[PDB]
Image: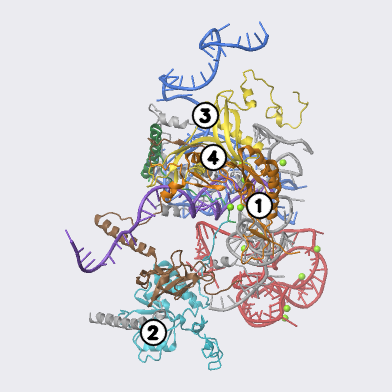
Chain colours: A brown, C green, E yellow, F cyan, G orange, I purple, J red, L blue
Amino acid sequence: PHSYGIRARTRYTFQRGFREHGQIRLSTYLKTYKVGDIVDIKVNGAVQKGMPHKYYHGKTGVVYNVTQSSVGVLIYKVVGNRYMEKRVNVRIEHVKHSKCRQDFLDRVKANEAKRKEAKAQGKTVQLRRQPAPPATAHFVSTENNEPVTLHPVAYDTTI
Amino acid sequence: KSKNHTNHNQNKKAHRNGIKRPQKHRYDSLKYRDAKFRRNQKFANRGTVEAIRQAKASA
Amino acid sequence: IAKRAESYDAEYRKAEREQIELGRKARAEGNYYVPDETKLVFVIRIRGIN
Amino acid sequence: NFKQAANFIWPFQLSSPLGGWRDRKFKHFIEGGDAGKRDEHINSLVRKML
Amino acid sequence: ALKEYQVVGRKVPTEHEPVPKLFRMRLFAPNESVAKSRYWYFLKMINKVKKATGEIVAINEISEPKPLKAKVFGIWIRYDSRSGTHNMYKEFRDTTRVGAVEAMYADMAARHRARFRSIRILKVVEVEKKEDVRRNYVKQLLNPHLKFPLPHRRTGVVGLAGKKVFAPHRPST
Amino acid sequence: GIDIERHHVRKSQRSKPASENVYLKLLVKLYRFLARRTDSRFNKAILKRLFQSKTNRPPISISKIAALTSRKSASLEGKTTVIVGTVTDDERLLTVPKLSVAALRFTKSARARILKAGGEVLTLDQLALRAPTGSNTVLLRGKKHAREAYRHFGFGPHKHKAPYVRSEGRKFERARGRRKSRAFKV
Amino acid sequence: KNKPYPKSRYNRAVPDSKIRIFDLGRKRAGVDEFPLCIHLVSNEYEQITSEALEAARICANKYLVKIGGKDSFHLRVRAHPFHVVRINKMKPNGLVARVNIGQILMSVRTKDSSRATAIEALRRCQYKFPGQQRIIVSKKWGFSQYARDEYIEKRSRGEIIPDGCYAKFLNKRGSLQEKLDLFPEASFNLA
Amino acid sequence: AHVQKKNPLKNKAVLARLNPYAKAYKANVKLNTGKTPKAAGEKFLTVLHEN
RNA sequence: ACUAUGGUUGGAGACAACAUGGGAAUCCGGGGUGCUGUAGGCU
RNA sequence: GAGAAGCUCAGACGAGUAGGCAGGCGUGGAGGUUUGUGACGAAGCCUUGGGCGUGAGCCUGGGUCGAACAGCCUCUAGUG
RNA sequence: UCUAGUGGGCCAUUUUUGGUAAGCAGAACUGGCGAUGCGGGAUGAACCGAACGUGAGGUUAAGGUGCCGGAAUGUACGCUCA
RNA sequence: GAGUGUUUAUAGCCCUUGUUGUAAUACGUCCACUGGGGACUGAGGACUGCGGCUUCGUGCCAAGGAUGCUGACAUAAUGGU
Ligand SMILES: [Mg+2]
Ligand SMILES: [Mg+2]
Ligand SMILES: [Mg+2]
Ligand SMILES: [Mg+2]
Ligand SMILES: [Mg+2]
Ligand SMILES: [Mg+2]
Ligand SMILES: [Mg+2]
Ligand SMILES: [Mg+2]
Ligand SMILES: [Mg+2]
Ligand SMILES: [Mg+2]
Ligand SMILES: [Mg+2]
C-alpha cells in the first residue's frame, strides 16, 4: 500500500488556494534573481513544468544558476548521518525571494547608519540586538481605577 | 516472519557522528552553470588575469 | 579591593532601602508599586541522568 | 561582563539537601513538589545544599 | 499550613486599552507562589488573560483581625466528585478564617475523598447572628451554659513514662 | 552519574618517533629541549615532524628546492632550506645552483651535486647551532599525496580514481560499467 | 474504536439501522405550548447502538402516551447511528452512535404541568442505554436557543413569528421592507 | 600550592586573605532611631479587609 | 475547543481534574464597499 | 642525579555483550650475556608455614627427591 | 585510511491500524533491556529512583518507620464493621 | 423557683476611634555577632605563597594538609593466616 510516484501524497500540497485558481499574477515573471539570492520554494500546481519534487516545497535555499525561465537553487537535505548538497532546477513560478533577506539587508544598513553617526558624535553605538529583558519597575495608580474583588463562581447547568 | 522494518534506532545512529555538514568552499565548479555563461567567463577571467599581470609589471 | 567592596555594600543596602521606601509610599497612597523583575536566576538540576 | 564572569565559575557541586526534599521531588513546586520555578524559595533550598 | 493572601493583578496594558482594570482576590495558599498561581487559575476562567499577558501588582498576607475571638465561619464551595460538580455550604467554628479553611479541606478529604485540586472556595464569611447558623451542631456551641465531659483520648502519661514498655498497674479513669 | 559526551578525548598525534634509530633519538632530545626553552614555532614544527612516519615525511628533490627558493618575488636568495626528510637529486636539472640545505638525509647524488655547485649540506643538529630558532629559514615539505596509494583512495562510482588491477589492458576492468556500450559508464 | 467508518462508496454494503423514526408526539406543534424541555444527556463517551436507541424510543413512546396522551409531548431522538461496527461472519455488522460527553440523547418538550412526568419517562430510558446519563431541565424554550425570560420579552414585544413547530426570530439584517411587512405588531424603533 | 581548601566562612584568617573589607564591615546598623511613622493609608486598609 | 510537557494524580474503565506552557474555528455584533503606477486628453 | 624511556605540579573522569586496540603474565626451543644455581642436592612433587602483585603469576620455610637448571637482552613456536 | 562485529530483537509511555479478543500481529515518538549492577515495587530483563574504580564520613532519591525490619504503637480532623 | 420583659445595674461581652507608643510578641530575613556537645579524617614532608599581628626582626599566628603532653603493655596488644 505504498506507491513512490513523484507526486504521491501531494493532494493538498500542490493545490491552489481557495478562490486562487486561474490566472498567475504576472509580477512573478518580472522578479529578478541573481546568484547568491536566498529564495523560498513554493510549488504552483498550475505550472506542471519545472516543478521541484515535493521534498523541496516549503524549503529555502541559495540561487546558484540562472537560465531563461528557471533558477538553480542549492538545498541541503539530510540523507543519513550528513547533509547532501541538492541542486534543484525550478521554474520561477515556484520561487520567491526570502523576505528575511531584505530584513537582514536593511538591519545591516541601519547598523552602519547608526555606527557612522555614533562615531561622529563620539559616542557608543550599541548595535547588538537583545532578548526581551525582564520588565522594569512601574507605579500602577488606582485613582478612578479601584480594584474589583472577584470570587470563584458557583456551578450551574447552562443547557 | 520477515519484512521487519523500523526507524527506532536509526535516528539515534544518525546523531552518533552527528548530522555532518558538507565543507563549504570559496569556489564551486562551473560545470553546474549554463554553458554559455561558462564559456564567456573563461574569456573574461583570462583578460582580467592578463590585465592584472601587465599593470603590476608596468608599475 | 577593600574600597570597591565597601561601595558594593553601600550599593546593595541603598537599593534595598529604596525598595522599602517605594513600597511604603505606594501603601500610603493606595497605589501599587510593581518591583523590578529579576535579572538573575539560580538553577539547580534535580533529576539524574537517566 | 556577566557572561564571562558566570562562565568562569565552575558549575557548583552541591550536596544533597540536609533535611531532604519534599515528599515527592518530581512534581511542580506549585503542586507541592520540587521541580520548576520556586521564586525566593531557591534560597532556603540552597542553605540545605550548600 | 495555609495562609490567606490578597492578590491584585491586571492585564498588561496594550494600545487598545491602556488602562486595564485591576482585579483582586482573597486566596488561601501555603505560600505566595501558590497564591499567584491560584490567582491566574481563577482569572483565566473569567477574563481573557494569562500569566504571559498579565501581571501581579500586589500581594499581601492577611492576618486575622481577632485571633482570640471564637467565631462561626460559613464557607461556600464548589467541588468536583467522581461523577459531577456540586456547590455545598459548610460551617465551622474557629478563631481564624485560615483555621476554618484548613478544617474544610480536611473535612472534604475525610467525607468525600475530595482533593485540593477539586475544590473551589466561593466565599468565606464570619456569621454574626445565631439564627444565620444553618447547622445545629454549630449553634449548640453558642449556648452560654454549654457543658460536656472530656472527650475520649488514650489517656496521658507525661512524655517519658509513656515511653515505658511495662506498667506496674492497670490504668484507672 | 555525569552526562559527559567524549569525542576528542585521547589526542591522535605521535608523542615520539616509532623509529628505534638511536641518532634520531638524539635529534629528538635536542629538539625537545629547543621547542620547550624557546618561543619559536619553527622548533615545535621540527620536533613534531621528527616523530612522523615515512609516508608522512615525503622526500623533496634539489630541483624543487631550487625552484621554491628562486621565485620572482622570493627574497629567499641566501637562506637555508630545511626539510625533515630526505633530499633527493633531480638529474633533469643539468646545472645545480648554489644552495644551502638542512635535511635528515641526503642521497649520495644529491649531496655530491650540492657541494660541487658550491653549496652546503647540514644535518638538523648543525642547523640548530646556526639558526637556533629557525630565523631566516625556508621550512619545506615534500608532496604527501604523490605516493601510489592516493591514486586509489576514494575509488567509487564517478570518483575517477584508479582501480586495483593485477594487469592493465583491455580485458582488465574496461567493460560493463566502464563504458556506455557496455550497460553503463561508472 | 477506530476512526469513523460511515456508509460511503467505499462502504456501500451496509445494513440499515434498526431505528428509522426519530420524531414523536405532536411533531407539528407550535411555540406557545410545550414551553418546558427536559434533556437526557450522555455523561461519558459511549457507543449506543441503533438497537439500543430503537429499544429506548419504543419504550419512551408507549409509556409517555399512556400516561399523558399524544398531544402533551414532543419526544425526539437526537443521537443518530452513523458509525459502522464490523464483525467476522459466523464485514459490517451494525450501526452505532458515537456520542461525546454531554451529548443529548433524547429531548422532550412538554408542559410545565407535565414536568414530573417528563422526568420519569426520561429516567426510565437510562436502563436501555449503556453508560451513564443524567437528566437536566433545559433553560431554553422548547427547542429554541433563547432563555425563558428573553423569549418572553421577544414574544411580548411582538418579534416572533410562528412557523410550524419552530419559528422566525427577527434580526438586524436584510431589506427593511420585508422585515416590516413580516412583523406587523413589532416596533422597528428608530434609536 | 593549595593542598587543602579552607572555607572562608569558617576560617577567619582565610576570610581576611580574601575580602580585605571584612574587618571594617559593619553589620546591624540602626536606622529606626526616629519616630517611626506608620505607612498604611486609608484606601489600602479598606481594600485589604474587603469580603 | 484543541494541544507540548508532569505526577507512585483521580477513576474498574471510559475519561476527568489539576500543574508549567501554546491557543483555534464557527456564529454573532459593529465598521467598510477599491487603492494605486506610467503616459496623455478635458470648463 | 634521579633509567629525559627520567623528574615534577594540577584538573576531570571510571557500566559493558559482540567487537577493536594496548600493556603485561606463563610455556618448549635458538643467539648473547650473568668469575649465574647445583650431588654440601638440579628438576619435579607435597605442605595443616612466610612474603609480593588489582590480576595473569612470582619468591620463600619445612618435607620428599636424585642430575640437571635459571635471571637479563634478543630469536622462535606444535605456547596457556 | 584500513578493518571488526552486526544485518532474528524485545519492553514501557504516548499516537495508532488489523483483530471478537489475546501474554496477538503491524507501523509512529521517546526512554529502556539486549550490553545495566545498585536502592525500591515480598518476587520479577524493561515499572519507580539511580546508572557502578578501591575505601572513610556526611546527606539523600524512589520507598518506608506495630513485629518480622533499619526508622514516630508520631501529631491533627474525620470516615468505615465486612 | 420558671417564664417574662427593660441596655449596666452589685456582672460581663461585641464594634469604632485618642496616648504610654518607635508597645510587645510571633513569623520572615540577614549579621564578614557570639557560646557549647558528638563523630570521621591528618593527604603533604627543609625553604619559598597570600593574609594577619608585631617590640618591625631571618619575630609571632589557627595564614600553601597534626602536633603536643602522658600512661600501660611488651609468652600482652595490634596486624596476618
Ligand atoms: Mg537527619
Ligand atoms: Mg520522597
Ligand atoms: Mg497529557
Ligand atoms: Mg516519570
Ligand atoms: Mg570499563
Ligand atoms: Mg615444541
Ligand atoms: Mg630440590
Ligand atoms: Mg592440599
Ligand atoms: Mg597487594
Ligand atoms: Mg596447540
Ligand atoms: Mg526497628
Q: Give the distance between the C-alpha atoms of the residues marked 2 and 1, in whole angstroms.
A: 89 Å
In this figure, which residue is indicated by the disc labeled 1?
Answer: G46
Q: Give the distance between the C-alpha atoms of the residues marked 4 and 1, in whole angstroms.
A: 31 Å
| Same chain for the residues under marks 2 and 1 in the image | no
Indicate which label's residue lies in the foreground, 2 or 3. Answer: 3
- Image location (x, y in percent) of residue F175: 54, 90
Q: Chain of mark 4?
A: G
Amino acid at pointer 3: Glu
Q: Residue furthest bottom?
A: F170
Q: Chain of mark 2?
A: F
| Foreground residue among A134 and A87 | A87
In this figure, which residue is indicated by the disc labeled 4?
Answer: G148
Indicate which label's residue lies in the foreground, 4 or 3. Answer: 4
- Image location (x, y in percent) of residue J15: 63, 61
Q: Is residue F184 visible?
A: yes
Indicate which label's residue lies in the foreground, 2 or 1. Answer: 1
Amino acid at pointer 2: Lys
- Image location (x, y in percent) of residue G170: 47, 46
* Numbered disc 4: secondary structure: helix
- Image location (x, y in percent) of residue A90: 43, 74
Q: Chain of mark 1?
A: G
On screen, A151 above or below I41? above
